[PDB]
Amino acid sequence: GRRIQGQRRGRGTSTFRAPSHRYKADLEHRKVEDGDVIAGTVVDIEHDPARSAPVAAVEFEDGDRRLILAPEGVGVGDELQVGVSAEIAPGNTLPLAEIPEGVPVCNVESSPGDGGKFARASGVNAQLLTHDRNVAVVKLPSGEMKRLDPQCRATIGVVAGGGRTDKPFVKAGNKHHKMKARGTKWPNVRGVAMNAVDHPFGGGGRQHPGKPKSISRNAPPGRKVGDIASKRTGRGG
Amino acid sequence: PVYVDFDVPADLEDDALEALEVARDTGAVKKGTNETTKSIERGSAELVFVAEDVQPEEIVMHIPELADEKGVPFIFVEQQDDLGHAAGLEVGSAAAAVTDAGEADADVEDIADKVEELR
Amino acid sequence: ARSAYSYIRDAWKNPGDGQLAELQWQRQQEWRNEGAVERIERPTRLDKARSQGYKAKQGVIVARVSVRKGSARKRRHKAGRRSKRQGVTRITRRKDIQRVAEERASRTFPNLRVLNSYSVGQDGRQKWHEVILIDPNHPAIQNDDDLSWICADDQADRVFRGLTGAGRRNRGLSGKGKGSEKTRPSLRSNGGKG
Amino acid sequence: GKKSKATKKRLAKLDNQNSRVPAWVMLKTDRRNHKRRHWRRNDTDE
RNA sequence: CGCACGGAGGCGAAGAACCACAGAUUUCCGAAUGAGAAUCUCUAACAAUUGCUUCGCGCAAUGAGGAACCCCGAGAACUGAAACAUCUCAGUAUCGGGAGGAACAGAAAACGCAACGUGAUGUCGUUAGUAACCGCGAGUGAACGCGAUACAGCCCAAAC
RNA sequence: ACUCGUACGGUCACUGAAUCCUGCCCAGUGCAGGUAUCUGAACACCUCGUACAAGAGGACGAAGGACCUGUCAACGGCGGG
RNA sequence: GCUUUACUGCAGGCUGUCGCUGAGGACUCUCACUCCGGGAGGAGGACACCGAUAGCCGGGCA
Ligand SMILES: [Cl-]
Ligand SMILES: [Cl-]
Ligand SMILES: [Cl-]
Ligand SMILES: [K+]
Ligand SMILES: [Mg+2]
Ligand SMILES: [Mg+2]
Ligand SMILES: [Mg+2]
Ligand SMILES: [Mg+2]
Ligand SMILES: [Mg+2]
Ligand SMILES: [Mg+2]
Ligand SMILES: [Mg+2]
Ligand SMILES: [Mg+2]
Ligand SMILES: [Mg+2]
Ligand SMILES: [Mg+2]
Ligand SMILES: [Mg+2]
Ligand SMILES: [Mg+2]
Ligand SMILES: [Mg+2]
Ligand SMILES: [Mg+2]
Ligand SMILES: [Mg+2]
Ligand SMILES: [Mg+2]
Ligand SMILES: [Mg+2]
Ligand SMILES: [Mg+2]
Ligand code: NA
Ligand code: NA
Ligand code: NA
Ligand code: NA
Ligand code: NA
Ligand code: NA
Ligand code: NA
Ligand code: NA
Ligand code: NA
Ligand code: NA
Ligand code: NA
Ligand code: NA
Ligand code: NA
Ligand code: NA
């Protein structure tokens, strides 16, 4: 048959790429030698086209002007600090070790100095639970307990723009506009609505998958479709 | 480095090279690794010199152990070009051998003794 | 008596033992950070180089080349093929890695010609070979009785036509009797069955 | 369209090639321009 | 005073035309090389990769072409087997790299008519559709030797 | 590539606004988890064989399978008497 | 052309083993190797990646 849509994706053609040239900033934590003597002032609050969430323009002491992944409650004029000795207030960034347990955090680093990887989407947050000289246990937004190096930096507070998901798109056009700002092909044609040549579920006199939807982890691309290595399906039991 | 098991102090090296110079003018000296190797094998070697900046090291790797199973004393020189100059060459030398000194036998003997002590 | 060279040779008989082993473990760290073709001032295996024709003279060049280990980096068929021709994984190229190394070196030095080459080890994913190249235009070589032969026009791009030692062995020309029916005088004249 | 100096030279040449075999060549050879090109009926290159 | 037999005019005994050899001139693009460009343009140029090196592009090299031939790599399918998978078509078509006037091969870690024998290598004739391979099906398929052609034998590494 | 992205994400599928709802079935097939025991290749190892080798056998045993469990808004099923 | 528990194979995934690969049937370490860090250095570590091979799955494809 023909390559399935999921296979066309990987080639990285225009249709599947994110409108990168239209994006504003790669939101990473600043690098500080040590000491913490790095503070800046929020100069503006802007919309981030890559995340449908606000972002903050900060002007640092040493003349550096950069956009920052903004937590809720950050405003123009506010002074933010980054470093070991940073104050424990919303919007500041310091290593997990300097953060008091039980405090909501966002933009958590996976490896110390990577600029942040976890809890960055609208209104989310990680929960710093356990401290130690060896490991800082953080609960990610998915509910998972993550063991991290206490040296991994993070920002105090929950990510801004919380509740974005609360409102329905209502119409195709609204989804369309959002989709145009992402690396995604939309709308979505169901496999079962296609011809056999185009998809493992295509074909038939009526619409139905011709086999069980639960596919093995070992299935090759072009065949891995439907419910991937599902431990279970449905709602009952 | 892989063939170097001890560090020769700058002052000892100076004495050694000076002895080599009076060795070429008085007695006899062999220049070059191939000619040095044969001295050790033929037993006509009294003191062999080995540079430490030899690249590749394969060229001189064998000198130490070969010397040991021949009773022939050996000393390390930091630079290849200094050994070549001391031997009287316009070019450098990875290894040299004092084949029978001369009006330096006193000093050479001491240098050999100073090295055995230096282990 | 034994030449000093015999000691370099003897060391290389077992590159995984003794001082040489420690040398390789150290060197390869630097080599893996070097490029595809690196010109080196002196051969790593002096005895082998001299044995193959190397001379500490003007116009004689040496370069270390790294080439990946393994079989053919082959693409699977994109049209009809009988089962026999559907393979990908087990297919290996007909030119040995050493020969690939020689060509990569010669390309790097377009004006030079390959004289010979030899192995200097490998790690888990690549092999290194040092190639001896010669400047057929330098008068220090045009006047050398032992090397001037390489200056002739018919020796141009000798490596690309398999006129190299590794080229000739890989072409099955080693044997002069049984087994060389389809190799001598050339693979092509024998219908490509060698 | 915007013609370049080189394109212009070529168009000029094509126009010149589009002339007729002079009257005297007929007499000299004791008796056709096989490359007569009309702007509408024919098509030039580029 | 080309093909080309017009008109006008001119050249040639200061030996023209014409032919041979040698030299002069030889725009732009073109490997195309200062940079860019559908043959033009912009402000000194071996661009790029290399060898030597007075370490300065100072001295040099490579690039691209050519009717096929030649050498080194990559390598189908129709087809045949009265289907078809190994096999066959075939190492063919086609593709990548490269030399020359011819390539390639070549002075035995050979042969093995086993010998008290031959004596570098191509090629031609033969050996022979033989030996060998093969759903032991269809098909596939040498060599030594011999008769010829032409003949040529040497240089390093190391020891010292 | 997704991605100047990080679970309020984005990938892979099914259904197809709202309203009232969405029953029973895990035997087969699929996916997934577990597994005393059974089965389970090659290398290395042991026995035999061979002055070596081919080869025969053994021991150990991964994923997988048997076996057990979960799962139908998973493929699907919801009859005769 | 298409399908599949048709025949035969081929990618791909999983898994053992060998090489890279090192020191003291469960374990410690650091030196290759990998990742993070501008750097200092940190994490991981003879595993993983990669090369080779073996078993299972394998109309994704011929
Ligand atoms: Cl969305
Ligand atoms: Cl060449
Ligand atoms: Cl004979
Ligand atoms: K066929
Ligand atoms: Mg970013
Ligand atoms: Mg939704
Ligand atoms: Mg788009
Ligand atoms: Mg749809
Ligand atoms: Mg339809
Ligand atoms: Mg299909
Ligand atoms: Mg329907
Ligand atoms: Mg349906
Ligand atoms: Mg021929
Ligand atoms: Mg006109
Ligand atoms: Mg130009
Ligand atoms: Mg047939
Ligand atoms: Mg038949
Ligand atoms: Mg054949
Ligand atoms: Mg024979
Ligand atoms: Mg000579
Ligand atoms: Mg990296
Ligand atoms: Mg099919
Ligand atoms: Na279907
Ligand atoms: Na070359
Ligand atoms: Na063959
Ligand atoms: Na026209
Ligand atoms: Na001319
Ligand atoms: Na040039
Ligand atoms: Na220059
Ligand atoms: Na037929
Ligand atoms: Na048929
Ligand atoms: Na067959
Ligand atoms: Na006879
Ligand atoms: Na069931
Ligand atoms: Na079931
Ligand atoms: Na059709």
Image: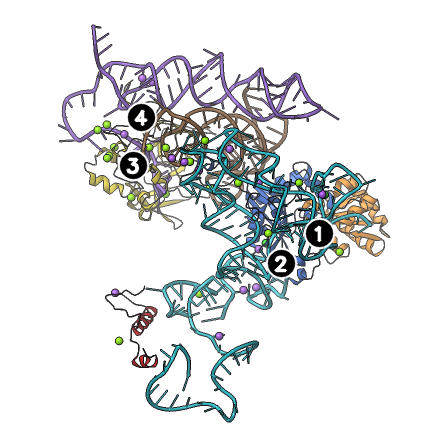
Chain colours: A yellow, B orange, C blue, D red, E cyan, F purple, G brown
Q: Is residue A145 above or below residue D21?
A: above
Q: Is residue E29 above or below residue C72?
A: below
The alpha-carbon separation of the residues under discs 3 and 4 comes to: 38 Å
Q: Which one is closest to the eye, mark 4 or mark 2?
A: 4
For the residues labelled 4 and 1, say whether their Cβ atoms are less than 8 Å apart.
no
Residue E52: give x, y in percent of width and height: 63, 61
**Residue where numbered disc 4 is placed:** A211
Residue E106: give x, y in percent of width and height: 67, 50
As shown in the figure, which amino acid type bears the numbered disc 2?
Asp
**Residue where numbered disc 2 is placed:** C135
Q: Which one is closest to the eye, mark 3 or mark 1?
A: 1
Instruction: Decide if residue B107 is on the left or right side of residue B52.
Output: right
**Residue where numbered disc 1 is placed:** B80
Residues at discs 4 and 2 both on one chain: no
Q: Where is the C terminus of chain A found, in terms of image quarters? A: top left
Q: Is mark 2 within 8 Å of ligand 24?
A: no
As shown in the figure, which amino acid type bears the numbered disc 1?
Gln
Q: Where is the N terminus of chain A found, in terms of image quarters? A: top left
Residues at discs 3 and 1 both on one chain: no
Residues at discs 3 and 4 both on one chain: yes
Which of these two is toward me, C175 or C2?
A: C175
As shown in the figure, which amino acid type bears the numbered disc 3?
Ser
As shown in the figure, which amino acid type bears the numbered disc 4?
Lys
How crowded is the residue under tag 2: few (<14 C-alpha within 10 Å), some, or many (20+)?
many
Q: Name the secondary structure under disc 2.
A: loop
For the residues labelled 3 and 1, say whether their Cβ atoms are less than 8 Å apart.
no
Q: Name the secondary structure under disc 3.
A: loop
Report the chain holding disc 3.
A
